[PDB]
Length: 372
Picture (cartoon, rainbow, N blue to C red):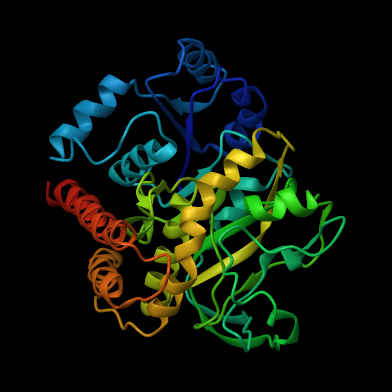
């Protein structure tokens, strides 16, 4: 019997619970809600109300969060006033021993009653199955949706790849694959970068293309808004800390762009696969300072293409996700000094070195829980 924990970090009143609780109550999943400093006492009351409405929801105060993190010798790992606190749920799910961790934004909702069931596709084992390859090494998961004005790419999709991608070949082949990451897609406002939402304000109308499993060597960004990770891969899913300056501008909003590529690079080196498609969620068009999104995303966007390129020519070592993830952190340190370009000021290069330390601090903590 497959156990599942859904992880959500929020500073809201808690109102999403009222419409989120159905899919998770019926499937008997656990919801881990990770509050921050600024989370009013509304949520906790919504937490306990929904609990004896049947739902297995837990909601640890910042105080409980910091007790746990001190015991794991990681008091400074996870900052406050940040959706990085997601990581606290990840850890808790992994300690309690769930099979499936689903990362959810406090912002979208299941559109089907089989939501939890379809995310269990990451516990079906290795089997031969249709596998999707792309001659350019990239796959565009938004091609699986009907958007509205024009075609779009996902947030985190590399920019150097987009012009030639229309001329790439897509294959499908029955081959051994082992799905460990299921990235479910989004109706309404699709997960595009700020550059794209300013330009075309896309609207995702339907899920039309079914689902796919990417061949080794075919990559695609994976966010943490509607994503199932098998407990084994959880170690490589550390949500990257934002705030590092690129040429003086502090990076924000790409912590899951890095997590999604890091777990994917890691999964593939271990013979595992990323899946895209169902279960789909609806993400309401809740617009805000789109210009401020852009200023926050441009620093990370200026780096990501060079980082991806160098990751393709860096072999990793390791037999499990922890060992592979630490290998990756060391590769990022070498990439940091090898890479060239106008955006690679000394603070940008140092960004890779600090995240690398932070990934190893994260794996250190996993090692302590698993040592006792």
